[PDB]
Image 1 (cartoon, rainbow over the protein chains, first blue to last red):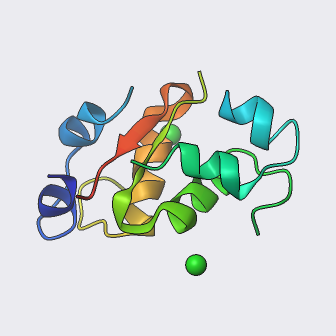
Image 2 (image 1 turned 60 degrees about the vertical axis):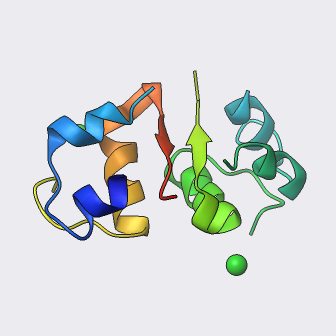
Length: 21
Length: 21
Length: 29
Length: 29
Ligand SMILES: [Cl-]
Ligand SMILES: [Cl-]
């Protein structure tokens, strides 16, 4: 999930926005 | 919601925990 | 740190610290 | 600020900044 995508690997705007309400 | 409870008024542990998964 | 007026990033910080490994939802509306 | 490794509070900060008035869910598992 987010940690794998954005901490252990490099984040993106695309993915962050998937977690906005 | 949270802003009314914890910013405009004084927060509590009780209420913060209501927003934990 | 929790029994005070917590706004914006300050509120999100407290949710993060209280919730730990569970995480949380932040729904300001 | 978003196209890098963001961990713990740093990750929550970026969600907060990107999401703005919508808020977000932080589900580290
Ligand atoms: Cl603590
Ligand atoms: Cl911005």
